Image (cartoon, rainbow, N blue to C red; front, side):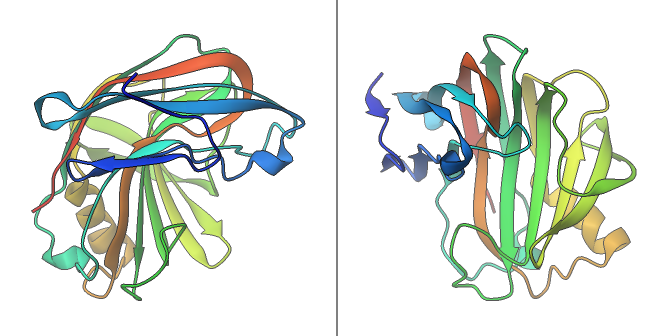
Length: 224
């Protein structure tokens, strides 16, 4: 690894991307740790991984290490034409409580801190060990060439829209996240014209299990 980010909130940024050993929920764990590794920044993308093991509180996320696309504040979702992204990843085992997911926050306050927003849009690419997303099942939606189970709910005052694979995982994926926002704008009244993009990330929410290792073979994210 080019960088080993094993400290709590260990951080790297470069080439318009950032990486965080985002162990935000660790104080619910009774044992374990996790490190995030920068493996490369080849071909306009990021290659990274995270190794971990956690015990305690199986319904509590301990971490969401992520790679994020750095963005300038104040971009209204309605004025973002495209958020094309691709990811290739593996997990070394699936007998864990964890997901792989894109995470996007938006807020009417363009200066909202990066830990949340008014809305959260997740696109899950894995759902291991019996975990659930926030909220309840809403409906199925056809986007990005796939069918998704959309779940909706709230985390505090933040409305959360999570698009889940009905079955299995998606280890090689590409989409335009604007398709997901557009769907929400049309059918869910998502107020894209007044929401600003806050974060644009992919990573893995880790609940319990391990030792496990998530390998992101490649990640790329653009927006226009």
